[PDB]
């Protein structure tokens, strides 16, 4: 559908759609108006990424210049965590009840099969 | 915002969409209803502020090759802003989308090499 809402790896993008079925039939991007049941759908644009491990961690935004990299520190901030896996169909959804308004960051980590890791951030807010 | 944008290579123009008569929410490439809509543009790269920028929003013909002929683009056109420099880096346009359907925003930048680059943002109404 749309091509505007995204997280980026260079030229390769992952399109994101957000909806909140308990509140509305509308679709959102980085300004999510309500607390509650939230579904985030990911559509990987580059077919080659379907064979690449992809991890998602959504954290409360600590508003620090540098994001924590330690797993214990990241865990303290974590709203939701999906371990790395290959998405062969190129698409997936996550559902979460956001009980609290605030700023959040979705951290998408790709593992190149050079074994190198790249992380991209999509920043959004709830409420 | 940080997620909603049209791309020129690695460069971005961030886009926010509102419908003030309907809701206090902000949208991106899915506009929920027909009617009064405001699209706000924020040009991230300072060098792009000195570049002529043209905007044409068309109904999406859903074909692999987009018409380039002026009559054909005009037949599909919802709104057209002639090329202009946005020195402040931001601007908004207001339009009443009367019809549900798929749309394409054609953004044309004129490099100071004088060559033109177009990017497309795709969205839908309803
Ligand atoms: Cu982008």
Image (cartoon, coloured by chain):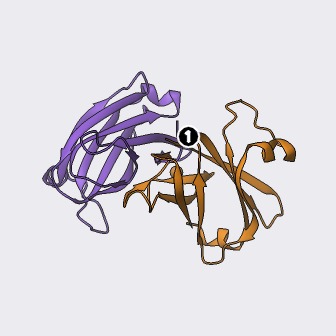
Chain colours: A purple, B orange
Quarter where residue A54 is shown: top left
Residue at position x 42%, y 31% in the image: A113
Q: Residue furthest bottom?
A: B88
Quarter where residue B67 is shown: top right
Question: Above or below — where is A65 with respect to A14?
Answer: below
Residue A117 falls left or right of residue B91: left
Could you say where residue A73 lies in the image, as x and y percent from the top left?
16, 55
Reading the image, the residue beneath label 1 is B100
Residue at position x 66%, y 38% in the image: B60
The one of A16 and B28 positioned closer to us in this rendering: B28
Could you say where residue B111 lies in the image, as x and y percent from the top left?
77, 63
Could you say where residue B38 lies in the image, as x and y percent from the top left?
53, 61
Quarter where residue A33 is shown: bottom left
Residue A89 falls left or right of residue B34: left
Local SS, label 1: loop
Question: Above or below — where is A118 with respect to A49?
Answer: below
User: In which quadrant of the rendered image does the N terminus of chain B lie?
Assistant: bottom left
């Amino acid at each position: 559908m749309g091509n505007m809402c995204m997280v980026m790896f260079g030229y390769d993008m992952i399109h994101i759609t957000v909806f909140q079925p308990d509140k509305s039939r509308s679709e959102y991007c980085d300004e999510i108006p309500a607390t509650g049941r939230t579904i985030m759908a990911f559509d990987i644009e580059n077919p080659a990424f379907r064979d690449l491990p992809l991890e998602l961690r959504i954290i409360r935004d600590p508003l620090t210049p540098v994001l924590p990299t330690g797993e214990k520190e990241l865990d303290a901030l974590t709203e939701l965590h999906l371990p790395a896996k290959k998405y062969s169909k190129g698409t997936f959804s996550v559902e979460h009840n956001f009980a609290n308004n605030g700023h959040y960051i979705g951290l998408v980590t790709l593992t190149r099969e050079s074994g190198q890791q790249e992380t991209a951030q999509f920043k959004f807010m709830v409420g």
